[PDB]
Structures are given as structure tokens and as C-alpha cells.
Image: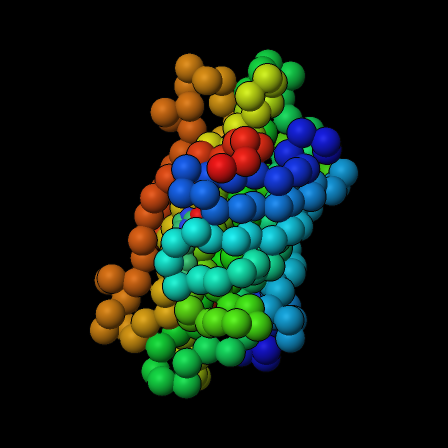
Length: 121
Length: 122
Ligand SMILES: O=C(O)CCCC[C@@H]1SC[C@@H]2NC(=O)N[C@@H]21
Ligand SMILES: O=C(O)CCCC[C@@H]1SC[C@@H]2NC(=O)N[C@@H]21
């Protein structure tokens, strides 16, 4: 899926590089502009490979665990969202970032936010 | 890693079958007991393959897009959470289910909830 496949940036200046496979897979790398992160992290996810043709977005999501060969934040973010095609293509998401915690600190394990991604072209 | 790998069930009786690669990959299938869903769906995700040394949980997350050979709900769920090992291992998660919508209806595109998984068969 050519629509989704490519390089994307969000409002924070973070970079998402993705390939959308015919079987519904998302694969690529994510670089965050912020937080306890440096360089590129592996991402994996899924997308609706037979969307409605109806002026609806394409549902998708992906996960980054924030461990690479440079740093380990002991945390993972999932972005859940939809892809909106056309000339000014966007991925509108909400996200959940969970950090590994003790049982006593589990109530404060999870941040929530929203990122909007613009495709670079 | 052996602890996350296995067959889990949540409070709804959904079945989450997963394998944790040495490297950080999660790969498996998900069968939901509820919603616009039947049979198994492909899932992939990631987890911290070197968790902290202080008895913290293991951060992890995965996605399912709700299309398989039977059905397509035009929606995707991501679970974000942590694995907590020991005697009664648990994966405690919060999730976001986004349905494809018009931009008009984008405000009402995303459900949020919370699932807890154990390896006890319903
Ligand atoms: O600090 C961490 O634990 C890891 C980096 C987190 C960066 C987050 S993920 C959601 C939000 N979107 C971004 O592009 N960066 C932040
Ligand atoms: O109805 C849909 O669009 C697809 C199925 C959604 C099932 C959800 S995912 C979150 C929650 N946890 C489950 O095990 N089932 C529901």
C-alpha cells in the first residue's frame, strides 16, 4: 500500500518511516524528537488492507518499544489511528505510552496523547 | 523470552496467543469474545527485551487490525501495557480501538478501555 508507505513527521518533529505490506503489516523505524530516546527504534503494526472506499480513513496502529542499541527507556508506545489519503495525506493518532513500573507505581505507568503525522513527498 | 510467550486470556474471555522474540518482537493471533469479530486475527507488537533490574514490569504493546478471511470491521486496536512475571503472571493493559471514519466523525472514532490478561483458561 503506496498510500501509507513512506516517511512521516509529527508535530513534535519525530520521524516515522514505514512500509505497508500487502498482508496488512506495518514495518519500519521511529525516531522521537522528545523523551528518553535517541536514534531509530523498530516499529511493527497492522493496518486495514481492504478499507471502505467511502471517504473513511484507514484504521491502523503500531508499537515502538523504546530499546535500541543506543538506549533503553523500559517503556513502549502504541499509536492507534487512521490514515487519511489524498494529496495532503495524514495519520491522525492517539497514543498510550506505558513504562515498566513496580506494582506500587502501576497507577502512574501510562501516559496518553495524540499525534498527527504528515507525509513527506 | 519464555514468560510472555504463551496463551493468554482476558476478563472478557478473548484469547491472545503470542510469541516473544529474543530481539523484542511480539507475534501472534487474537481472538475477541466480543465486538465485530470472529475467529483469529494477526497481531504484531514489541516489548522491552532487557527490562529493569528492580522488579519493574516489562513494557510492551501490540496491534490487531480487525480484518481476516471472515470479516473486516475497518478498525484497529492497540494494547499498551506491561508484563508482570512471577507466580500468577499478568499482562495489564490499556487499549485504543480506532474505527475508520469520515473526518466529520473523527471525534467519535476511538474507544478506550483496559484489559488484564492471565494464562488461566476460561
Ligand atoms: O521517554 C520514553 O519513554 C520514550 C520516548 C517517548 C516519546 C513519545 S511516544 C509518544 C510521543 N510522540 C512522539 O513522537 N514522541 C512521544
Ligand atoms: O468491534 C470491532 O471493531 C473489532 C473487535 C474489537 C474487540 C475489542 S479490542 C478491545 C477489547 N478487548 C477484547 O478482547 N475485545 C475488545
